[PDB]
Image (cartoon, rainbow, N blue to C red):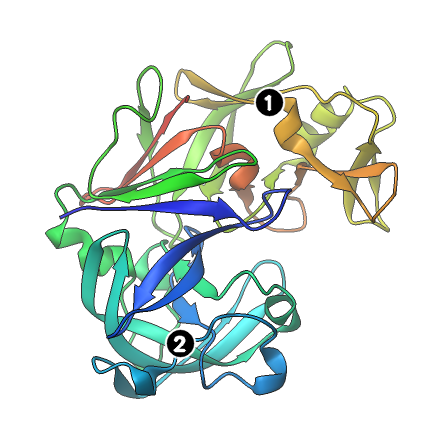
Amino acid sequence: STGSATTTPIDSLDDAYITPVQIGTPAQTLNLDFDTGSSDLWVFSSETTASEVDGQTIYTPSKSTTAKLLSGATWSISYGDGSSSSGDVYTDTVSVGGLTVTGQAVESAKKVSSSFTEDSTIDGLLGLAFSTLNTVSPTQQKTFFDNAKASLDSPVFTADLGYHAPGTYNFGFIDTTAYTGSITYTAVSTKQGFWEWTSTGYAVGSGTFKSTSIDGIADTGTTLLYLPATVVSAYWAQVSGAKSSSSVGGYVFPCSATLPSFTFGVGSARIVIPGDYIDFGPISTGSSSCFGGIQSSAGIGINIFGDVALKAAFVVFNGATTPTLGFASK
């Protein structure tokens, strides 16, 4: 089997991408944030505290003839940005782009943190990291990809995120028309539960490539590119007037600037992020200070190849017995 679904930016900045997902019988379609940095499929629901729902579409398990309470199971998650959610668990039929999993754990939110409530466009998350990170207790549950893997034509999914435009998530096949050149594959460590890999270095604009190992994670659920402070300083030094602002929370730059590209290495291959992809717009409406899309990871504990980096590539998440990642230009 295969599946193919379009993923759409939630706003004009590509802050996140939503993909429609059919849950239950008859189908209830919710727009979920596919997140290769986490491993829970959780949704706003008829069980979510009413004051914490503000425009999201909800899953109502009582209206699904295939829903079954997973007795005794609870979940609770906290994300790198400080947001969180928790609740109970149903199993139900879940389909993405024509690919159907029966008995998928659908984690129904009883509580969500304010950042979720305040974003009416995201109805939940669909985690695509390794199932060892799934938070369901006392019986950990499998991700949608883990449940589908054995049925897929090939045990892979691909992320093809658009710049200011829709893109595609495919399951079970590699669309050879979706990229240019070849796909360069690179080793993955699953020891932390992430799609963790080592970039071979970077360049700023037309500058020389610096060969240096940068361990980080491929994370579709993170908006920006978070890298070591040395690398980030080297980038923003090429933008007149750019500076790190403690009060804003990162590097800002004059909105009148033209940003240089940023290149990252994948083995001997190179992925070029155009400068425009690094512009996240005014820090507040009407400001001439703009927020940068490359930020320091120093306060995180891990480097994160988020959407800013991934949208410059066609990315293969290869879930074979020994997982690997592939990157191609497009």
Quadrant location of the C terminus? top left
Q: Tell me the quarter of the picture where residue 326 sits.
A: top left
Disc 1 designates what residue?
A: 274
Q: Amino acid at mark 2?
A: Tyr
Residue 197, how many percent across, how many down? 41, 37
Disc 2 versus disc 1: nearer the observer: 2
Q: Secondary structure at mark 2?
A: loop
Residue drawn at x 67%, y 50% as measured from the top left: 299
Residue 287, how many percent across, how many down? 88, 42
Q: Is residue 197 left or right of residue 85?
A: left
> Does any portion of residue 219 appear in the rendered image?
no
Residue drawn at x 38%, y 81% as measured from the top left: 60
**Crowdedness of circle 1 by 10 Å Cα count: few (<14), some, many (20+)?**
some
**Crowdedness of circle 2 by 10 Å Cα count: few (<14), some, many (20+)?**
many
Residue situated in front as seen by the camera: 229 or 183: 183
Image vertical order of residue 39 relative to residue 330, above or below: below
Residue 311, how many percent across, how many down? 49, 34
- State how many labels appear: 2
> Does any portion of residue 195 appear in the rendered image?
yes
Disc 2 designates what residue?
A: 59
Residue 152, how many percent across, how many down? 14, 48
Q: CA distance from mark 2 to mark 1?
A: 39 Å
